[PDB]
Image (cartoon, coloured by chain):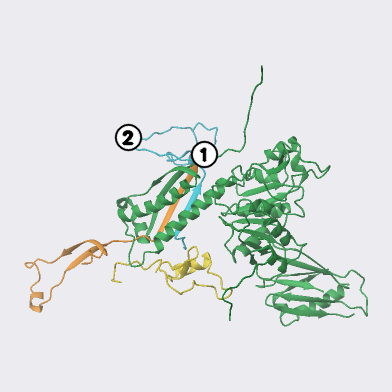
Amino acid sequence: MWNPIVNVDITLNTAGTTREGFGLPLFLASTDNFEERVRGYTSLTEVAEDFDENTAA
Amino acid sequence: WNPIVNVDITLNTAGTTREGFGLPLFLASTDNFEERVRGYTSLTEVAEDFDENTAAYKAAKQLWSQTPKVTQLYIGRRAMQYTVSIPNAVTESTDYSITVAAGGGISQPYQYTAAENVLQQFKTQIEADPTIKDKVSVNVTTMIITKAGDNDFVKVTTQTVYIASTTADTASTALAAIEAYSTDWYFIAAEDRTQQFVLAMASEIQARKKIFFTANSDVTALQGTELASANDVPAQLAKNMYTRTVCLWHHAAAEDYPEMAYIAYGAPYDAGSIAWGNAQLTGVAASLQPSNQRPLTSIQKSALDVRHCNFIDLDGGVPVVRRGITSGGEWIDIVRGVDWLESDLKTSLRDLLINQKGGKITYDDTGITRIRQVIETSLQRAVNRNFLSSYTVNVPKASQVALADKKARILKDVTFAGILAGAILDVDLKGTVAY
Amino acid sequence: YDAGSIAWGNAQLTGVAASLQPSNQRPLTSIQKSALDVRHCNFIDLDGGVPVVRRG
Amino acid sequence: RAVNRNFLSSYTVNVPKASQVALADKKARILKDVTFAGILAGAILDVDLKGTVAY
């Protein structure tokens, strides 16, 4: 499909950098919001979609 | 033949023009010209296509009251529907006539010299007309006339018959049709001040990169301090978090248009370098209560405050527009500066990419460093205005890009960040006196 | 210029106006440009006031 | 010569061993199985960018 020669997007949020190390955490929660027994997330926003604010996860 | 030296020396005062980021556009219900958009560079030109009582001339006069004066102004035409009815009983040996015009200079008179039967006669004549039947629609029950097929312009005019007109399209359709014909404008204001149209227009501009200015004279907005309970137009605008909408409460926001006066205060100047608060608009009085015609009390001002709505205060003896904030809580300055920054980056990278005749920008680290450099220069330009105060840029390595990007000749994953400056608008002071 | 060392996209042409719709002389919209993309047909797009043959 | 123009970035060439070519081609004076490969240089035409503003 047609694309602008230059595409620019700007938002008023705030962001920080990540860093890589040894080992990633896992949280063993009691929930049923999804079928698979393990699922990954890369920001609090994604967690908020499948979990509300009062959930332990 | 022309004289060696030519001199005019007209006996008229003149002012200076200045230009900045974005030109305004006023969207009004009119039928004075066919094109859905036109451009005027002075008020006198508006006086040619309009008179002193039309909303468009009012808005044009308000906009050019400020100094320095905006470079140009645009006017947009909304789709219209007409209605015809006989203000008298059906009478024989009595005349009934109208005229129907369409886009392209078409015009056709219709006559039935003898109430439903006269309208039906007109409808049949129109539908049997060689040309008008193709591009005009008629319905009768009273009569109505609207678009048909592609045609974009229609007019009706005629003593024994009556004619009235009203806006037919909604905000979304009108805005789409106007954008289809002219993309050069940043500020937009609307003549219609109904709740439905105002909200529909606010919801549309929120999905683009523009700013929508509107006034309001609803008295219920002055009372309810609880934002949850309030349901006037400013309260609903605040509730939806429309950061790209601007509301200015004013008593005279039914016949007059202070929105253009507010727009002219910041349009001539550069984006991100001026604060829109505490402005002094020339020729505009302070916000007054519709009853008792006295300036607003502190309680009413607080009620407007909880709705993120602007007002024309009165500091001692001088009126000043307060806090210049959009309904979403953001300052107008931040939004305008962000849009200017986006445009500047989009122009700098365009200039880098287009002017490579006879060469390339190879897909490797050397090519990526040039893109780094142009972006850094563009951000430094914003830092020079005292809009930002720092920034950072990150770019991917050539040995890390995917194959699909190389096949499509597109670079992704470029990101950056910045920090804002701020300003001062209010002061708090305490002191003491003693022997 | 010599072969193989020049990208033909983003070309600027002197005196050639941007592609316009015959009906109303307006520059082609985004929808119409996408129609040409699936047909692998070039067109004279518009930057901010500068015509350019984009894909090549 | 192609690499010098920046058209390519590398290449390889393969030829048959003279001791393995079938003796039918040796009578036809025809050499087959000569092949090569190249890696295109590429270029950039479009750009995508994202950013944020905060205090």
Residue located 87% across and 77% down the image: B96
Residue B284 visible in the shown view: yes
Residue B42 spot, x, y in % from top left: 66, 63
Left or right of residue B336, residue B409 in this image: left
- In primary-sequence order, the first of circles 2 and 1 is 2
Residue A33 spot, x, y in % from top left: 51, 39
The chain coloured green in the image = B
Q: Residues within 10 Å of mark 1 (few under 14, many from 20)?
A: few
Q: For the residue marked with disc 2, what is the amino acid? A: Phe
Residue located 35% across and 61% down the image: B407
Query: Circle 2 is placed at which residue position?
Result: A22
The chain coloured orange in the image = D
Q: For the residue marked with disc 1, what is the amino acid? A: Ala
The chain coloured cyan in the image = A
Q: Residues within 10 Å of mark 2 (few under 14, many from 20)?
A: few
- Between A40 and B247, which is closer to the camera in this rendering? B247
Provide the chain ID for the residue under circle 2. Answer: A
Colour assigned to chain C in the rendering is: yellow
Residue B78 visible in the shown view: no
CA gap, disc 2 and disc 1: 26 Å
Left or right of residue B367, residue B37 in this image: right
Provide the chain ID for the residue under circle 1. Answer: A
- Residue farthest along the front direction in this orientation: B4
Q: Quadrant of residue D17?
A: bottom left
Q: Which mark is residue A48?
A: 1
Left or right of residue B399, residue B413 in this image: right
